[PDB]
Amino acid sequence: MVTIRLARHGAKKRPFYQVVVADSRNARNGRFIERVGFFNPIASEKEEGTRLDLDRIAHWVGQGATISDRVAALIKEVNKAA
Amino acid sequence: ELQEKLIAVNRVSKTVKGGRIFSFTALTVVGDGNGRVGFGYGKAREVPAAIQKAMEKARRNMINVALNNGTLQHPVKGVHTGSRVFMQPASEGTGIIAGGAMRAVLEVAGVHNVLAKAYGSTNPINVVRATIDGLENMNSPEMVAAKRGKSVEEI
Amino acid sequence: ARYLGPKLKLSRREGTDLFLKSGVRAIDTKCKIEQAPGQHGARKPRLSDYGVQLREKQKVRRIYGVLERQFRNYYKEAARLKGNTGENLLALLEGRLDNVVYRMGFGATRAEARQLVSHKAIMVNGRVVNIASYQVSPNDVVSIREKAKKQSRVKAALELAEQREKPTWLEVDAGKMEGTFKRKPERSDLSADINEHLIVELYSK
Amino acid sequence: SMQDPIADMLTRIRNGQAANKAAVTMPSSKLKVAIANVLKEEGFIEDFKVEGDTKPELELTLKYFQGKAVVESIQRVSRPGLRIYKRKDELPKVMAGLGIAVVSTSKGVMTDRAARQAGLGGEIICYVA
Amino acid sequence: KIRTLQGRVVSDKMEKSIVVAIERFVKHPIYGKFIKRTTKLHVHDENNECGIGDVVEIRECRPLSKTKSWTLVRVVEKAV
Amino acid sequence: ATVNQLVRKPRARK
RNA sequence: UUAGCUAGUAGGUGGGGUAACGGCUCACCUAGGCGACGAUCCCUAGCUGGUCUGAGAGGAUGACCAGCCACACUGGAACU
RNA sequence: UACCCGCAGAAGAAGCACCGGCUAACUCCGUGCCAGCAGCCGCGGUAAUACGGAGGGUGCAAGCGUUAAUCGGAAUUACUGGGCGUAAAGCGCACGCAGGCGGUUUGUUAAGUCAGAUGUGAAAUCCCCGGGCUCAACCUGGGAACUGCAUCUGAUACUGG
Ligand SMILES: [Mg+2]
Ligand SMILES: [Mg+2]
Ligand SMILES: [Mg+2]
Ligand SMILES: [Mg+2]
Ligand SMILES: [Mg+2]
Ligand SMILES: [Mg+2]
Ligand SMILES: [Mg+2]
Ligand SMILES: [Mg+2]
Ligand SMILES: [Mg+2]
Ligand SMILES: [Mg+2]
Ligand SMILES: [Mg+2]
Ligand SMILES: [Mg+2]
Ligand SMILES: [Mg+2]
Ligand SMILES: [Mg+2]
Ligand SMILES: [Mg+2]
Ligand SMILES: [Mg+2]
Ligand SMILES: [Mg+2]
Ligand SMILES: [Mg+2]
Ligand SMILES: [Mg+2]
Ligand SMILES: [Mg+2]
Ligand SMILES: [Mg+2]
């Protein structure tokens, strides 16, 4: 189904995640639909490393897109820091 | 003041009743580094006698050519016996890229930045003759403005 | 990844001062400077058109101690950068971290200045970079760490470069044991007799 | 036969320029006037006149320097066997901007220097080198 | 407004259908010469009014048979 | 030599 | 050093058929269909985003990554 | 785990190929068209820097050479950018369909072409400016690029009807 999940890019021992919309039948780096944002778990957190766009998020959640718990944590803290 | 360079040395022979008598052929170029190239040719029994007679022809047979701050005005075609010469001026700081034959001609004129490629025959004496004659029919923006007659941006 | 042979033997092969030693003892009081190393050093060798591009390449690479695999990668960067190729070639050679320490005078020789970078003595904006091939950004300040100030390799080197002339773009402070890399150097600010166009033509074929 | 009359026009110009002829004549057309008038306005030739209405005969006055060819070489580019078209940014220059390239567009016949302010493309006629 | 092709009829023997050939000019990807390329389509002809060589106007429709995907609009010129 | 010849058959690569 | 190929083949009516249009299938009717802009036959091959080479135009190729199609001992069939 | 503190002492840590020309570096001895060498040119039957060895040097580098394969060099299938009097090549000649191409003047169409705009050309790769991993490789932000295709509005000089 239409879902919001992560795609692990980056080299070995350097995790990095892409915020895309895809189907449940595709893999982690499988056939997505559109790029939404990005996530850096090894970010220094003094600068850039987490940026999304709530306008593209509300366009698909209103259509009925499911959200994973790891991506939903970014949703719960995008309103605390901004 | 003159900048000289030897190009190639080729021992040739002459057949007589007693057998074979050898000699030497030398092709040289000179220049001032400011758009004046004069090439000569030598024929003598000995190699330092051969290159010196080529230098004696090099004082005369020397032409003028309009440089543009050390590079060509425009790309120009060169044609000879088997030397299809295609040159093209480049941007600042590219350096001289050419064969060993064309490098002797381009250094003594002061030329720095040119594209160069020779098609056909690889005889170095045939390459340089199209190179000299390819520069004398190469023209300047001032002398084509003497043809056209306008002191506008094209100058 | 270095060269362990004799230093001035490379200058006996080339015939050019390469600043391979300090400068206390003269260049000619140790070896015949115009003698090639070996059996026929007094015999004058022939120099072809292929040589003058090769002998110019060997002159610069023996100064900085950069091998062929890394020096070709410097040509991969200088070709991609805009402007003059040779001016961008000098930006990579002078912007090396072991050259900045050497031109300030913390190491008496380039072999000594490379070991000071390698064996944990140089701070770059308060951070220790233990590799000698770091490209130094402009407007940075370098310094000596607190444990390496008492070493005699710094005390003996602050007077030999003081006798020689200093570059313009560097700000050497000997009391605080620090320095500043201000701006990018130019062609005329460096050695004028080194012709960078001879090296590019060999990598242009 | 006479299937490319512009190439027949360029043949008569290049011969008389080299053979020291003072003036040449040729059969006229609407397109040959629209090219020779451009060459008159670009300093390559001197004057052109029309003669005859049922047999239109065009004339060209040559141009020399000290008896030297002003138009050194000219190259027909497009041809009835192979048509050449370029866009407003793919217009080729002749001798890196020294010579002009005759390009006919919907705003009349002009040069690539004049097509910069016009911003159009079309058929390349000849490289006036 | 809608997608519309134009061409001429080369065959009309079959009932309720005609064969319309479409020609187009193609720049060659290697040489650039403009070459006539023939596209032969099968067009549904209601009431069979089209003859041979008629310049005709056709539009796009659903597939009606194994080979047909085009239908009729009107004839521009007939039986000249 | 003619471009219209190479429409029928291109240059034969060995 | 492959020039003619094709009878469910090409089109139409009606019935049947699938989730959907349709020779997809059946009886009947018509003799057309395709093809020197390469039909048909034979051999070889997964394709593409790309990689590499090259000043460029081009050239060679499709491993790792991603997209799609096909396949799951060989062949055939249907259920769910 | 990376990282960092502390200890000891240069202590634990350099080889391969080449050296007649191409192509960077020269002498000596042994061998005697034999042995061998070799990518090309071709070296060696009594003085071989080319064989074998030694001395010395050069080019690379924790790698170095060789073999096989692809492109470049090769403008050596030449669109860019080749030729056909004698180097390979103009059918022995002629008619002629299909095909290609076509004088000049005006009107029209806007087909080809050109201008503008929309949609699209997945991401990754490459390119531009950045950021991060001590550096680099590598990862990554945005932009450019993807020279493509479709549609619409235009211009009418040229080509086509
Ligand atoms: Mg691993
Ligand atoms: Mg002479
Ligand atoms: Mg040849
Ligand atoms: Mg039915
Ligand atoms: Mg896998
Ligand atoms: Mg796959
Ligand atoms: Mg040598
Ligand atoms: Mg050996
Ligand atoms: Mg002997
Ligand atoms: Mg290594
Ligand atoms: Mg091979
Ligand atoms: Mg080629
Ligand atoms: Mg040839
Ligand atoms: Mg012959
Ligand atoms: Mg005959
Ligand atoms: Mg009107
Ligand atoms: Mg993409
Ligand atoms: Mg992207
Ligand atoms: Mg990227
Ligand atoms: Mg960095
Ligand atoms: Mg017309």
Image (spheres, coloured by chain):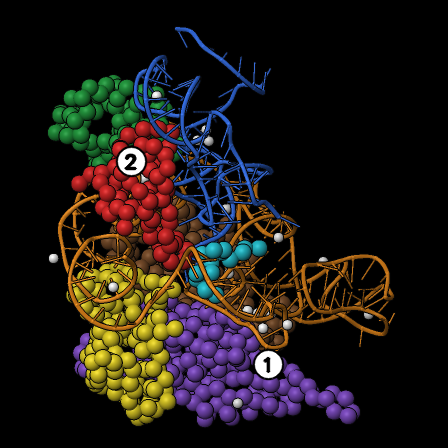
Chain colours: A green, B purple, C brown, D yellow, E red, F cyan, G blue, H orange
Q: Residue at x 38, y 64 (%)?
A: D81
Quadrant position of residue E44: top left
Q: Is residue C154 visible?
A: no
Q: Quadrant of the C terminus of chain A?
A: top left
Q: Residue at x 52, y 84 (%)?
A: B28
Disc ID at residue B9: 1
Identify the secondary structure beneath mark 2: helix
- Residue C13, position in %: x, y? 54, 68
Q: Residue at x 25, y 37 (%)?
A: E72
C-alpha separation, residue under disc 2 versus residue under disc 1: 87 Å
Depth check, front residue: B111 or C61: B111
Q: Are marks 2 and 1 on the same chain?
A: no
Tell me if the residue at label 2 has its CB under 8 Å from ligand 4: no
Q: Is residue C10 visible?
A: yes
Identify the secondary structure beneath mark 1: strand
Q: What residue would you read off at disc 2?
A: E48
Amino acid at circle 2: Asn
Quick check: H21 above or below H152? below
Please tell me how many numbered marks the rendered image carries: 2
Please give the chain letter of the residue carrying mark 2: E
- Residue H76, position in %: x, y? 54, 62
Nearest-to-viewer mark from 2 and 1:
2
Q: Residue at x 31, y 32 (%)?
A: E16
- Residue C10, position in %: x, y? 53, 64
Depth check, front residue: H92 or E12: E12
Name the side, left or right, on which D104 lies relative to C136: left
Q: Quadrant of the N terminus of chain A?
A: top left
